[PDB]
Amino acid sequence: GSSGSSGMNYNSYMDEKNGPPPPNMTTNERRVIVPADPTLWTQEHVRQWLEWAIKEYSLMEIDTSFFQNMDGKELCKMNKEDFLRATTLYNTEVLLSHLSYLRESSLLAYNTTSHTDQSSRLSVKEDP
């Protein structure tokens, strides 16, 4: 007769080989600026934040004793008036705005999520 087999596979793959150190570039090392929302803050997040803003924004003459051990939730209840008693208006606008900016992000965080979640189980490694 007269018959054959005309048909190629045509495919590709990767080996994923990594060379010796040093590595490409660092990523993270126990560094966090915010947990999530201003309502779920800790006693430290209330301090580190202030010490940070005063540095970045480079403010001057601001109450610190007020944020020595204030509840993260209280920071939200604080209004232009409450904040005015702690610092000037110019500063109150720099704080309230920041605390309000974080919330503006949550507006997008609210997702339906159709069975697309993932558990967290990442632990640091060491030794050969």
Image (cartoon, rainbow, N blue to C red):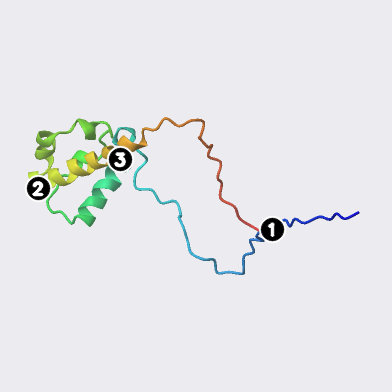
Q: Residues within 10 Å of mark 3 (few under 14, many from 20)?
A: few
In this rendering, is residue 87 above or below 3? Answer: above
Q: Position of residue 127 (x, y in %)?
A: 64, 57
Question: Residue 6, how many percent across, how many down?
Answer: 77, 56
Q: Which mark is residue 10?
A: 1
Label annotation for residue 90: 2
Question: Identity of the amino acid at label 2?
Answer: Tyr
User: Mark 3 and 1 residues: CB-CB less than 8 Å, in contact?
Assistant: no
Which corner quadrant holds the C terminus?
Answer: bottom right
Q: Which numbered disc, 1 or 2, marks the residue closer to the eye?
A: 1
Q: Quadrant of residue 12?
A: bottom right
The residue drawn where x is 27% and y is 46% is 49
Q: For the view shown, which residue lies furthest in the front direction?
A: 1
Residue 57 is left or right of residue 34, and the answer is left
Judging from the image, what secondary structure is the residue with disc 3 in? helix
Select label 3 or label 1 by which is in front: 1
Q: Nearer the viewer, residue 116 or 78?
A: 116
Q: Residues within 10 Å of mark 1 (few under 14, many from 20)?
A: few
Q: CA distance from mark 1 to mark 2?
A: 66 Å
Residue drawn at x 54%, y 66% is: 23
Badge nearest the viewer, 2 or 3: 3
Q: Are there few (<14), some (14-19), or many (20+) residues within 10 Å of tag 2?
A: few
**Secondary-structure class at tag 1:** loop
The image quadrant where one finds the N terminus is bottom right
Report, in whole angstroms, how far the alpha carbon at label 3 lies from the one at label 1.
Answer: 46 Å
Residue 68, image x, y percentages = 24, 40
Q: Hey, what amino acid is under mark 3? A: Ser
Whether residue 42 is visible to the viewer of this picture, yes or no, is: no
